Image (cartoon, rainbow, N blue to C red):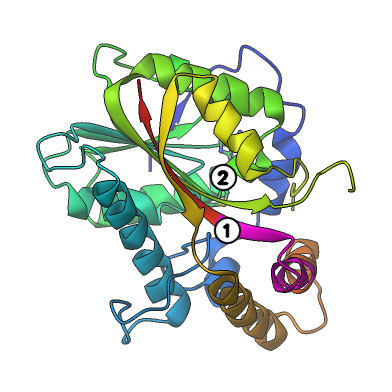
């Protein structure tokens, strides 16, 4: 199906590296991360659907839980407040379908991604679910969201679901500044990211480690209030999530043919140990535009 292209004024030297980690067919990825392709951890509580694959169910439940945190923290998330939404680093597109279902009167849902294979998959799912009129896909670096069409229609809602970690500090700055200009006051930003809880001096395009404080500063420097900040999911749940991903890799990619899946196994093992030692956590950040 159709994807719109958006100019890159500045040069993200890191972009082609990020693209290569997501370049493999969705048909392969399905066997590793589940049939809905959620790719930023899971919440494994009593509201999780027991009939879907744990990765699909825990992934959806994680997104739902973040909206509950945003709501409790006083985010403007009523059905009448969300007319335009953006999914920044949208992966295979599960959040686009989630947003379309949760906000059936949301006029415009923009997904931005640098991975063509991921967007071509998302395009097929959006097309087959009949959401093509509302959901728009952009082959577009997060730093270039300033050039997305119809600037007169402001963003009410922005999602950074495990995409932020791939950004250079410069791309993070350019993305947050551009989002600030395109988002109306009281617009909600929903962030999930793996952040380090130690000084980074001591240290899958997994470079550009960040901290809660580094992310907090990037938000407040670019006209966003942080209204909720906490560990989510728990280190225990994230280790469990990596466990399920590793079990799928052991089953389907035992002899580590594919370098991207070998790299993911390494991160699953190595980052799970960092989570065990409490050197890092998954964090939910809810912010709003000033
Ligand atoms: N500068 C950038 N601009 C756009 N997308 C980016 C980006 N850096 C990383 N990404 C994207 O961020 C995603 C990280 S994986 C997470 C995918 C999706 N948010 C989910 O929760 O399932 C990938 O799709 C990657 O291509």
Could you say whether the residue bearing mark 2 is in a helix, strand or loop? loop
Query: Which residue, given by chain and number where applicable, does mark 1 sit on?
Result: 282
Query: Does residue 148 sit above or below 287 in this rendering?
Result: above
Q: Position of residue 50 (x, y in %)?
A: 32, 86
| Marks 2/1: CA–CA distance | 13 Å
Density class for disc 2 (Cα within 10 Å; few <14, some 14-19, many ≥20) is: many
Can you say which quadrant of the picture contains the N terminus?
top left
Residue at image coords 63%, 38%: 213
Q: Give the quarter of the image for residue 184.
A: top left
Considering only order in the chain, which callout, 1 or 2, is on the residue closer to the N terminus? 2
Q: Is residue 72 magenta?
A: no
Could you say whether the residue bearing mark 1 is in a helix, strand or loop? strand
Q: Kindly check if marks 2 and 1 are in contact, taking CB atoms under 8 A apart as contact.
A: no
Range of magenta residues: 270-282
Q: Position of residue 215 (x, y in %)?
A: 59, 36
Nearer the observer, 183 or 6: 183
Residue at image coords 82%, 82%: 255
């Amino acid at each position: 199906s159709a994807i719109e292209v958006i100019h890159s004024s500045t040069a993200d030297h890191y972009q082609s590296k990020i693209e290569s980690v997501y370049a493999d067919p969705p048909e392969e990825w399905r066997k590793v991360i589940g049939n809905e392709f959620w790719y930023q951890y899971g919440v494994f509580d009593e509201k999780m659907d027991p009939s879907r694959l744990p990765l699909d169910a825990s992934g959806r439940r994680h997104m739902e839980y973040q909206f509950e945190l945003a709501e409790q923290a006083g985010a403007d998330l009523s059905s009448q407040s969300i007319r335009r939404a953006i999914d920044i680093g949208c992966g295979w597109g599960p959040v686009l379908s989630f947003l379309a279902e949760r906000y059936p009167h949301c006029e415009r849902i923009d997904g931005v991604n640098v991975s063509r294979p991921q967007l071509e998959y998302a395009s097929q799912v959006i097309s087959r679910e009949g959401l093509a009129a509302r959901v728009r896909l952009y082959l577009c670096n997060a730093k270039d969201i300033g050039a997305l069409p119809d600037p007169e229609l402001p963003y009410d809602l922005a999602i950074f679901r495990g995409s932020l970690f791939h950004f250079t500090p410069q791309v993070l700055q350019e993305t947050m500044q551009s989002l600030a200009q395109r988002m109306r006051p009281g617009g909600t930003v929903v962030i999930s990211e793996s952040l380090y809880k130690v000084d980074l001096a001591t240290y899958a395009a997994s470079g550009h480690r960040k901290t809660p404080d580094s992310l907090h500063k990037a938000l407040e420097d670019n006209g966003f209030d942080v209204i909720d900040r906490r560990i989510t999911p728990s280190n225990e749940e994230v280790i469990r999530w990596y466990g399920l991903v590793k079990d799928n890799l052991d089953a389907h990619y035992p002899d580590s043919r594919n370098p991207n899946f070998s790299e993911l196994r390494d991160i699953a093992i190595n980052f799970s140990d960092a989570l065990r030692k409490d050197k890092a956590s998954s964090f939910s950040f809810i912010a709003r535009r000033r």
